[PDB]
Amino acid sequence: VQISKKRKFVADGIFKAELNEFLTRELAEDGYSGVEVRVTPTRTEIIILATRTQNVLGEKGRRIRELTAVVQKRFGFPE
Amino acid sequence: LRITTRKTPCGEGSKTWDRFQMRIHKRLIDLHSPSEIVKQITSISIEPGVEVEVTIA
Amino acid sequence: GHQQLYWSHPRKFGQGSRSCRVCSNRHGLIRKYGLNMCRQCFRQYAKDIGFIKLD
Amino acid sequence: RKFTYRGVDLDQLLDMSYEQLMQLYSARQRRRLNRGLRRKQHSLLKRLRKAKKEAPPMEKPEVVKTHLRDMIILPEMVGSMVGVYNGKTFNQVEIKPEMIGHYLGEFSITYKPVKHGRPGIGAT
Amino acid sequence: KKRKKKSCTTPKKNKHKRKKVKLAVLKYYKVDENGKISRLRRECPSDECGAGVFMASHFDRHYCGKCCLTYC
Amino acid sequence: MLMPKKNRIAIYELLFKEGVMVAKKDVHMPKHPELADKNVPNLHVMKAMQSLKSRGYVKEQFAWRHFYWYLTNEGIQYLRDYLHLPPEIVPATLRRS
RNA sequence: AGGAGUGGAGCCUGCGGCUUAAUUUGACUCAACACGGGAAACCUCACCCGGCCCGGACACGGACAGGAUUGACAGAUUGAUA
RNA sequence: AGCGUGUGCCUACCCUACGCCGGCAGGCGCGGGUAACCCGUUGAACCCCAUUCGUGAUGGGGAUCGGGGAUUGCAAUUAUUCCCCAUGAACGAGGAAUUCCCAGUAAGUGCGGGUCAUAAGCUUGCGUUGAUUAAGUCCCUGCCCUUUGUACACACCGCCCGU
Ligand SMILES: [Mg+2]
Ligand SMILES: [Mg+2]
Ligand SMILES: [Mg+2]
Ligand SMILES: [Mg+2]
Ligand SMILES: [Mg+2]
Ligand SMILES: [Mg+2]
Ligand SMILES: [Mg+2]
Ligand SMILES: [Mg+2]
Ligand SMILES: [Mg+2]
Ligand SMILES: [Mg+2]
Ligand SMILES: [Mg+2]
Ligand SMILES: [Mg+2]
Ligand SMILES: [Mg+2]
Ligand SMILES: [Mg+2]
Ligand SMILES: [Mg+2]
Ligand SMILES: [Mg+2]
Ligand SMILES: [Mg+2]
Ligand SMILES: [Mg+2]
Ligand SMILES: [Mg+2]
Ligand SMILES: [Mg+2]
Ligand SMILES: [Mg+2]
Ligand SMILES: [Mg+2]
Ligand SMILES: [Mg+2]
Ligand SMILES: [Zn+2]
Ligand SMILES: [Zn+2]
């Protein structure tokens, strides 16, 4: 089945709030500024705004490749 | 949607209330056309904050 | 044995079966629209959720 | 003079099954029996029966202690010594035939009756 | 408020200490001079406890410790 | 903490395969969602990851109710030596796909 | 200038007292007292009575495949099939 | 009439039309709704029109108790809640004192939301009926300014004198 629009919008807001809190705690050291979630039926893109992107990406892109993993693990939507 | 809560984290002081409010707006459009043209026009429509649902009755 | 006794008491309804999704507190819980937050956490995260004060 | 529960004496009550006893009881006891008894109540009944079987012909059975304050007094319990927990101590109760249909917790009081003293300074 | 101690109960409830048995494998088998082996302890009829899982020779019962199966 | 060796093997295999671990901090959860058909309680995962963290093998973060764990290089070496994995095996994180 | 009142009655709920094994606790003029979103049968629970569990990471030492340790049928025991 | 809610990650617990059974609380079936779609044209209560009663603690009031029935729950006793017979207390407008209010307002009357397995004498909102009085003042209470006096500055809950 499906849920009502009220619950859907509330769930989207709660998801964005939790994502922002997690990103804050993770990337405070890197000057984390904000998060922007653009939802597309193909893929859901997440833009991370921070002062420096070198630390967020990590070496060879390891660290960011970790984050997009745990997010997929946390909220459960498919790989 | 409305949520009325108390401002104070505890139970001390004047009884003051916060009234939070969320508004949801909804539009409907009808089209007599084949699927392909609808997807053609819809592809551009992607906008941040707007949920678009296409159904064939 | 201990395996049967531990956590045996049913928790399918009541205050003991519900808690805040942020701080795990069972008091002052908001269940409307499936928020499942205590009032303090909700007041902290209302702007992020999308609730605006107009009056 | 002879005891009768809603026109039925003790012997017929002992002969009756649970379904027959449901119609004699009140609404709450009937609903409780219809929902059924769990393992702990059956264990208590078994212990009471075991204790009553081993009693001397002229002596009372050994006291059986329990925390089950919501147990319904069945006609098979008449004549048994039950210690009922009140949160602090086990109070000894002998089941009488006029207790049929009540709970065990109704016969072990959970508080001390109040005897008032002189009111303090904070009373006006 | 400050916590009161009130430390007085049954003197000491002791924890069960498991018995130390030296070479418990040996007593399961008996040996003749010819070199034969006879299994003193019965073997449980369960699936998992079929070959090496022996039972318990209690004074009035047989008990498998791995699946709680009991026989007279 | 006492637990069967196969639970530890499964947890370590999953951690080395993915490179990260997520838990909900629920000691009464009957089984970990990710570790299904292996019957691993969530408490075992929590305690195993805590033991790994105390030795520096994993890095930990906590968010809103959840534990997040990332694998360290020394943790990679420890898991590779523990599971007897060939030196040609790396977690999916270390592959820039 | 007035209206509806409260203070009087019965009852419902909070706060003092007094009892209790415990009757958990914060707050005391406005700016404490149907307030802590506090309408508690269990949970909530923070109080009292009694009984299990370790969910005491990690480092060092001891002991250990001639076994470190784990669980458990019956009878006893227990409020209890801890 | 109006504001709103409705099948839920964990999480078990939704709103209900229609048919039958029961006197009632309720029980059986069988459908709709993830909602301007179904409950729902939300047949609300006060109010309106008739009937009975007739200044009698009265057919006002409904406290306290007895006996039965049913629902929620793992569990209802120290009565969870609900229904039916029976019982029928103070109370005849309230001392000193004291609260809120200037128009769709005060008051009367119901209905939603929160709490909620069971659930409103509380709160937060919504309608419906709908006024008397006033368009002023500094008398009471309190708070601001200006002038003025001070031996106060931890600021009158101050400082300070003599037995
Ligand atoms: Mg009145
Ligand atoms: Mg009055
Ligand atoms: Mg009064
Ligand atoms: Mg008072
Ligand atoms: Mg306390
Ligand atoms: Mg003021
Ligand atoms: Mg209170
Ligand atoms: Mg209650
Ligand atoms: Mg009880
Ligand atoms: Mg209990
Ligand atoms: Mg309690
Ligand atoms: Mg241990
Ligand atoms: Mg009368
Ligand atoms: Mg009368
Ligand atoms: Mg009765
Ligand atoms: Mg009591
Ligand atoms: Mg009546
Ligand atoms: Mg209301
Ligand atoms: Mg309600
Ligand atoms: Mg309240
Ligand atoms: Mg004045
Ligand atoms: Mg002067
Ligand atoms: Mg001066
Ligand atoms: Zn919270
Ligand atoms: Zn066996």
Image (spheres, coloured by chain):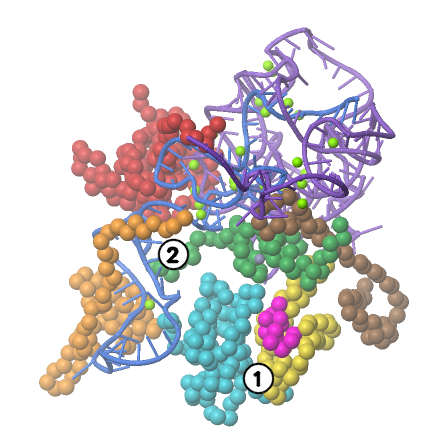
Chain colours: A yellow, B brown, C green, D red, E orange, F cyan, G blue, H purple
Q: Which quarter of the image is occupied by the C terminus of chain B? A: bottom right
Q: In this view, does C17 lie to the left or right of D17?
A: right
Q: Confirm or reject: label 2 Cβ below 8 Å from ligand 10.
A: no
Residue C7 position within the rendered picture, expressed as x and y whole percent measured from the top left: 43, 57
Question: Can see residue A18?
Answer: yes
The chain ID associated with circle 1 is F
Q: Is residue D102 left or right of residue D58?
A: right
- The answer to which quarter of the image holds residue G30 is top right
Q: In this view, does D67 lie to the left or right of H106?
A: left
- Mark 1 or 2: in front is 1
Residue at image coords 34%, 49%? E4
- Main SS class of the magenta portion in the image: helix
Q: Check if residue B42 falls in the magenta segment.
A: no
Residue H30 position within the rendered picture, expressed as x and y whole percent measured from the top left: 66, 49
Highlighted magenta segment, given as a residue range: A21-32
Name the mark on residue D38.
none
Q: State if disc 2 and disc 1 touch (CB < 8 Å).
A: no
- Please tell me which residue lies in front, H6 or F42: F42
- Please tell me which residue lies in front, A4 or A21: A21
- Where does label 1 land, which residue? F93
Q: Check if residue A31 falls in the magenta segment.
A: yes
Looking at numbered disc 1 in the image, what kind of residue is underneath it? Thr
Name the mark on residue C5.
2
Question: Can see residue C36?
Answer: no
Looking at numbered disc 2 in the image, what kind of residue is underneath it? Leu
Residue E42 position within the rendered picture, expressed as x and y whole percent measured from the top left: 22, 71
- Please tell me which residue lies in front, H161 or B11: H161
User: In what element is the residue under mark 1?
Assistant: helix
Residue at image coords 24%, 57%? E13
